[PDB]
Length: 405
Ligand code: HEM
Ligand SMILES: CC1(C)[C@@H]2CC[C@@]1(C)C(=O)C2
Figure 1 (cartoon, protein in one colour):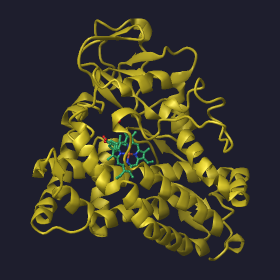
Figure 2 (cartoon, rainbow, N blue to C red):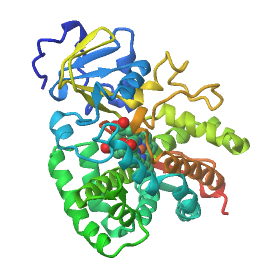
Figure 3 (spheres, rainbow, N blue to C red):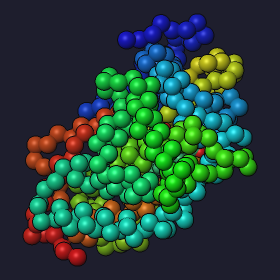
């Protein structure tokens, strides 16, 4: 299902990439996307899939477009257009200068100081989860750790019942990796049905949780509206439920396959932070975009007002112009160049939280379970979308090679 080419698009710029179902998926999602960076592909292409949209394939172009909010607006950041149209999260569907006041509040809730405060819980849960799995000699990493770990921490931050995970998680997934089961607008509405009553409750009778802080916050010297709060909280939930969860599975799949990298971290722990950056470069996983506010000529291509462009965060660090041997994991790279957390005014506020969850997992898993592999005859499947993911990750290990702490 290819849309007919608009008049302004040169046929030589056509490359029919389906961000939801790329051709090479079997090879790995990162590898499936990297097809865009082969020599046969121009820097900026038009795909006929998902209603037709531009895709910038190079880190330089991506960064430039992200900086340029004048031309590339956040108003409609999702593809397909119906999803980007329905999208009304704050701060993300706003451009500067409006965005700024909303970002400042969201930072209050997810920023550095919050991470510092939650550090002990993060360490506590990681350890508990790992210790609980250790003696089993096998898990489903995705369901057994990658989901519960970051999710439960978010549920704690937010003050929401763990009971709601399944329902919330389902809705979040519909937004980033649509099934066909529900439209974005439907998913969005259902999440909103969930939040509304809670926000109300928390405006009346505030807590210390993230939702209470957001619901009662000040923006541009006046109180936030219920609608604004609902829209911020909807974003926090997606970021909380759908990001770190998927990343940890890519990273663990890779460590399950690379004894030598596991070892390096065990002996030279000072390298964990560097390693984290390298893994965030190699297993980058987000791809959203922007909408042209006007006609604009960008790197010699004519963009029409209302055209959508995908600016895949994932691709910058995979670009050979940015990192030599991009597909190779190297913990001692002199420069780890990526835009995994985004770029420009919408740089991820949850990044500090994400890095602390990642480093804790690596240190604590490797301590207890130094030696593991993917289960014999398990075929690992990746899924593509706005945020890419791993379907299931069967791991096996000999309990006798583990260490209790
Ligand atoms: C592996 C982990 C994560 C990655 C790769 C990531 C990636 C991103 C990207 C690429 C953006 C920019 C989107 C744009 O420009 O349209 C973004 C923004 C954002 N993310 Fe993160 N995210 C992660 C984890 C988190 C977490 C844990 C949270 C907190 C719940 C979160 C909250 C946010 C917020 C609030 C913004 C919007 C900032 C604004 O628009 O000013 N993210 N994230
Ligand atoms: C692209 C994102 C990763 C960022 C945080 C959650 C997400 C799906 C958004 O809608 C903005």
